[PDB]
Length: 293
Ligand SMILES: *CCCCCCOCCOCCNC(=O)c1c(F)c(F)c(C(=O)O)c(C2=C3C=CC(=[N+]4CCC4)C=C3[Si](C)(C)c3cc(N4CCC4)ccc32)c1F
Ligand SMILES: [Cl-]
Figure 1 (cartoon, protein in one colour):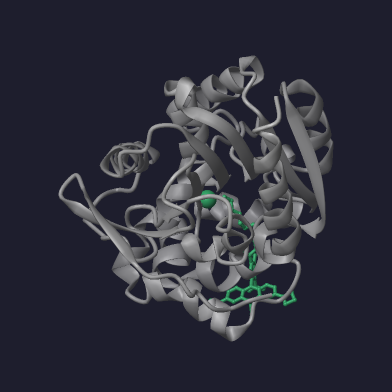
Figure 2 (spheres, protein in one colour; figure 1 turned 120 degrees about the horizontal axis):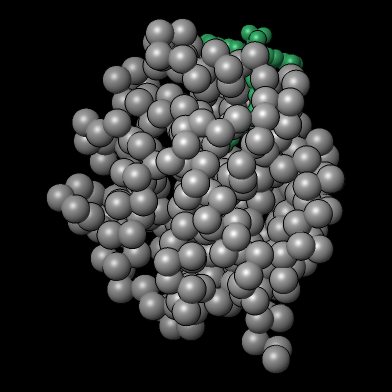
């Protein structure tokens, strides 16, 4: 499993800030937009993009405040991410896209798709944000930690002061061990504690047990949209999962129209780090099937 990030930096001005993105593959055709979540960057896509790049343009931005993107003094609310990702997409002049989305990148992608349904030709998604009706529907092993994250004094001490999301939670969302080189790539954007705001706001935005109400509403609205939409869908899932346990993937594979589900074997949250060759190969082959009517 490759540790290298062999992609030239691309930058675009977005709302008076600069965002970093990977941009590889042919210039023409429908682009494939890859959206990472918490607490990763375009680095999470590094071993999946090589399967897609031969046939499609691959675009993998770093969310505002993350990766090699700028770090303005925001609260990094989901609303901030929405504002910046909307402006990113318009800044590149993207018309129709295929979405490949994960964790908070999936909340961005589904929310955008809902608002721009004629521009989304396909969605591949994994370990995505859905409402977690109660804390019992959150994995027991992660329950105490995410409950602690979702306070101001304790949460901010763990995530901002001690960097527990990067040093602890991240490696514990992968079944295989992350190497030191991989950890250093994930650490790089957050070496300065003041830049860790996004790592703390994100778990505080998770729609868990009806809170926060604004995120719960927005997430229910896109999961309704997704159940009504004929858009081609590709769902990767792992055992035991974190956001998406196997029973939920089984349910969505049937409830979502035009949905193919693929089992990656053992995984938790960062499925990309446990089976990148399967995810990359299935995306590439599924993209080809979008052109078979
Ligand atoms: C969008 C949704 C994203 C989900 C991504 C994450 O998926 C859920 C995974 O949740 C894991 C929750 N658990 C922890 O974060 C955690 C602990 F609760 C915990 F008690 C400990 C611990 O100290 O034992 C660790 C942990 C840490 C914690 C802190 C830390 N540092 C601060 C400076 C260094 C380092 C670690 Si490490 C990588 C040495 C570690 C290793 C293990 N194992 C089991 C075999 C090696 C276990 C825990 C920790 C937590 F990460
Ligand atoms: Cl999170």
